[PDB]
Image 1: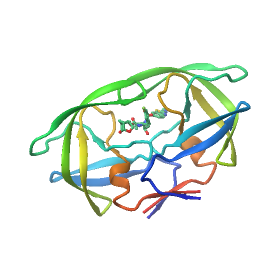
Image 2: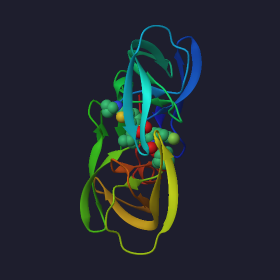
Image 3: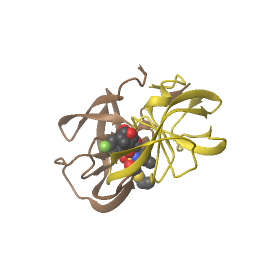
Amino acid sequence: PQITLWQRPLVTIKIGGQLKEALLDTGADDTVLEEMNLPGRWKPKMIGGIGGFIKVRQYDQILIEICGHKAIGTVLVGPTPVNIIGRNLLTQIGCTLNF
Amino acid sequence: PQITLWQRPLVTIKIGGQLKEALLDTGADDTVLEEMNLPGRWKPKMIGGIGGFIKVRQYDQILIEICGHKAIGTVLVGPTPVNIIGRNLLTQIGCTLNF
Ligand SMILES: CC(C)CN(C[C@@H](O)[C@H](Cc1ccc(F)cc1)NC(=O)O[C@H]1[C@H]2CO[C@H]3OC[C@@H]1[C@H]3C2)S(=O)(=O)c1ccc2nc(NC3CC3)sc2c1
């Protein structure tokens, strides 16, 4: 689809068997999801944004379905205020900015 | 133009007579720029992101030229780590997401 930006660009995702909403976020390098139950091993990581840093769990080779498009990649899980789909997954579903 | 997301979507802006680079950020409601010299009155505001809040100065009806497109609107100025162009200005230059 084409998405204008008069509202937040929220989409439905399926990850770890669960349905969630997430923001398509071109300003995010990585994908960061609110605390949730994912299986398997992970590695600690710290990421920074406008107000400081947060500690997240890094999961690799995670399957995520984003508005009906499948992608596999790294997902960070931790105390983000909003679920974010970052460029690591936006590139895999073919997402572009246009003006 | 059309912009893919394999790199950060950075663009040149002109604001307050000064040239800067900024991220086209669909995950940002508002536009937030690093400390800089702007003329005129402003109002204090606090905004939140991944790691907490920051205090910014809110300037209204500011002219900004974003990759050669003029827009007028609110610009927030404060300790953001990156210049961000948010949806309040992205809508005025006709920017869309596509996949
Ligand atoms: C540069 C910065 C923009 C990146 N952020 C992406 C922006 O899109 C965030 C998304 C957001 C929305 C709401 C919210 F509550 C919190 C965050 N928006 C944001 O702060 O906006 C603020 C501000 C704008 O006006 C209003 O609208 C939303 C909210 C409010 C005030 S990030 O989330 O910090 C990020 C994400 C992924 C990532 N991956 C990394 N990987 C390391 C490098 C390898 S670093 C890293 C950092």
